[PDB]
Amino acid sequence: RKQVSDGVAHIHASFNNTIVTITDRQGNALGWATAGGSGFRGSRKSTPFAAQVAAERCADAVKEYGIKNLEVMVKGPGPGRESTIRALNAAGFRITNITDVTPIPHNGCRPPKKRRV
Amino acid sequence: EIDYKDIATLKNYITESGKIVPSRITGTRAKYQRQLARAIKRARYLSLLPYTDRH
Amino acid sequence: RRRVIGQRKILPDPKFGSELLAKFVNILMVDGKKSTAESIVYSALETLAQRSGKSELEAFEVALENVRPTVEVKSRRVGGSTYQVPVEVRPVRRNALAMRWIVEAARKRGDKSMALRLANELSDAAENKGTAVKKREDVHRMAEANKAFA
Amino acid sequence: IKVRENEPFDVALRRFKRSCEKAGVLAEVRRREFYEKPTTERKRAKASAVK
RNA sequence: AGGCGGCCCCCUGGACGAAGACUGACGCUCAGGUGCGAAAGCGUGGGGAGCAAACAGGAUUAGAUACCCUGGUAGUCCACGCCGUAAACGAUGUCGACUUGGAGGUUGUGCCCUUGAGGCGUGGCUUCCGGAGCUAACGCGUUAAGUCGACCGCCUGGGGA
């Protein structure tokens, strides 16, 4: 459509996959990518590593909107919730602020099944 | 002063995550901490606080 | 469970004091005979000087550097089924593998005179085609996929 | 959860992990424990001066 | 007892206190009786977002009418009744009095500049350790499995039941 030079980057992390979607203030997506859709399967799809590729695949789909400065919003408990922030900061962007919608730690879920020392 | 229904008093007993603080900084002499921790939850229903910071 | 054993420096060459050449004869040694390597040593560099050999300051040390191993792996485990991981090799290993890669690439098909089969490979060691390069890229296409969960 | 702090870079150092509470170095847990030790060692015994 | 939980205003049994007053053994337990439900189920109609026996499919395996994954009915909820069973567990039947200790709470009431992060008394509760006592040994320990008494039920090797 027409460039806007401002928006929000939403990182939504599940125990199997990670979604990276950039939105405008009118309440819609500009660009989306996922850790699975970045060519990852099984125990690789559920990594913080596959989420770092999703930032550069979202950067390839938001190209039309003229955005260089954006703020971050983190969602979900999954393993991709931290690793991809600094990778998006390396994809041709500047991060103005960081926020999250994390509950306080009482829900538990997914013991690590890996090392750990 | 001396009551929980004033936000400039109330904000001294809670965090930037909506949580209640330890007794060591409430001035309750460790004897009214139980009642103050309930008065802070009562402030949510008096339109002074949101029910959780994440919403 | 810790090997790491001793310390072994080996001897240099008797004619110029070379450390690389005195090691390269230990790759061409077969049946415990070093004489067969001394028929290939200097003669490959002098046969390169019949086709393309320009400058000899390092002899063949830069052909062994244009030959570039990168796709070495190890196996990681916590029980039965294992997980492959790539490894960043030391220059002493990178050199030891490059010395086999080129003499095994020169042995790939049967022909006359190993000094001449190696000179044909050293004339290629300025552009590196087919042998010692086409298998590398076909396994390097997993080199980051085998880092994902460490 | 905090950690909203705007560093564009991953740091090559430990700053908040494995050294303060819930193990290691402080508040150690499991990895073999001893139960006669608290009913054996009560007062020093050494440190004045070994040298 | 089972268990009880967002807040706000109600309806309401019990318990605890201080000064007085009025009773004058009114104290304990109880054969057979007479009564409480966590969850799931039923009797009758409503209500139906999660979720979920069954149902309906997929995967796995040589097989899988199971695990696991994807959909999903009864049910969960409300009224008027039924079911009366549980780790109902603190594996500790029920009434009182008697008893060297340590450490931490909950709530009345008396006297004090509370000139004390309250203090010293006096009442009712309540938690983690620990010594005398108990005991096959584990476990109990002033809220005892201790100590001295009152009362009601059951057991006598297990399989078979």
Image (cartoon, grey):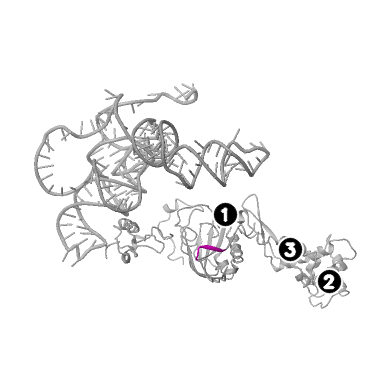
Secondary element under disc 3, as helix, strand or loop, is: helix
Q: Chain of mark 2?
A: C
Q: Count neighbours of disc 1 (C-alpha within 10 A) and say few if under 14, some if 14 to 19, many if 20 or more.
A: some
Amino acid type of disc 1?
Asn
Quarter the N terminus of chain B occupies: bottom left
Image vertical order of residue A42 relative to residue C50, above or below: above
Residue receiving disc 2: C123
Closer to us: E154 or A97: A97
Amino acid type of disc 2?
Ser
Closer to us: C87 or B4: B4
- Is D18 inside the magenta-drawn segment? no
Q: Are marks 1 and 2 in contact (CB under 8 Å)?
A: no
Whether residue C73 is visible, yes or no, is yes
Residue receiving disc 1: A16
Image vertical order of residue E80 relative to residue A73, above or below: above
Residue receiving disc 3: C137
Closer to us: C60 or B40: B40
- What residue range appears in magenta? A25-30
Which tag is nearer the camera, tag 1 or tag 3?
1
Quarter the C terminus of chain B occupies: bottom left
Which tag is nearer the camera, tag 2 or tag 3?
3
Amino acid type of disc 3?
Glu
